[PDB]
Image (cartoon, rainbow, N blue to C red):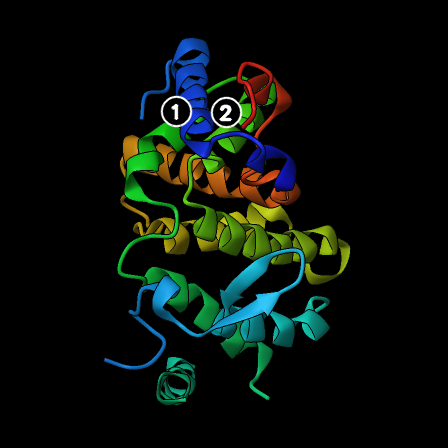
Amino acid sequence: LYFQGMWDQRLVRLALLQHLRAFYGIKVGGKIFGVPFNALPHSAVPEYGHIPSFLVDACTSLEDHIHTSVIRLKALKNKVDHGSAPPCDIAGLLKQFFRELPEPILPADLHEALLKAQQLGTEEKNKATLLLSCLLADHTVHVLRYFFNFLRNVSLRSSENKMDSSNLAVIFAPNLLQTSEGHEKMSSNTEKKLRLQAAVVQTLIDYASDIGRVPDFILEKIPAM
């Protein structure tokens, strides 16, 4: 995201926040699991930068199965936490990984904003949501661009695996946002929130390649370095 690097990020940030209010009214013990993801072993990944090695290796292992017991899952988690798997279990570990992060990778302060974005009209949800992703720390931006690319790829092959972006979002959203799951006795309010939280994640999947990417109408308002 070189082109946007030609602007003082400080100002880019101010301008994003200004547009979000003006235009939309949105005002803002082991080795792997539970560790802040920035503190984990990273691997240089091309066109994405440095991404945590667990993520890279989990996703890369599932690459070949995109078409496709918590006792057995837990054993693998422990082996991984201590330092080939069935694909099911890798997937299972990816969900647990995000759930167990000290802080949610989509930070809590953005959640309301993200949900608000998801009440806008179709065309404008997408825009707002993507503007919100540009508020993310750029390490996060790169980890998320990588992961959402992986997700997107699963989704694009749904004729086969049956997991479209809606289907994936429902599953991952609670793990990414670190929220509760759907249940039977849900209030009308609790459930609407769930759906919209999944909708956030679904948008992120569908527009994976545009995550963290500042639009020209933002940049246009500012002079560059």
Residue type, numbered disc 1: Lys
Q: Which residue is mark 1?
A: 116
Q: Secondary structure at mark 1?
A: helix
- Residue at the spot x=27%, y=36% of the render? 187
Q: Earlier in the sequence, mark 2 or mark 1?
A: 1
Can you give x and y, in whole percent of width and height, for residue 64 in the image? 72, 74
Q: Which residue is mark 2?
A: 128
Q: Nearer the viewer, residue 78 or 10?
A: 10
Q: Nearer the viewer, residue 1 or 54?
A: 1
List the single residue furthest toward the top. Answer: 22
- How far is mark 2 from mark 1, CA to CA? 9 Å
- Residue at the spot x=63%, y=41% of the render? 2
Q: Quadrant of the C terminus?
A: top right
Q: Is residue 205 left or right of residue 9?
A: right
Q: Are the residues tagged 2 and 1 within 8 Å (C-beta)?
A: yes
Can you give x and y, in whole percent of width and height, for residue 203 in the image? 56, 37
Residue type, numbered disc 2: Ala
Count the numbered circles shown. Answer: 2
- Residue at the spot x=32%, y=21% of the render? 27
Neighbour tally class for label 1: few under 14, some 14-19, many 20 plus, Cα within 10 Å? some
Can you give x and y, in whole percent of width and height, for residue 35 in the image? 30, 69
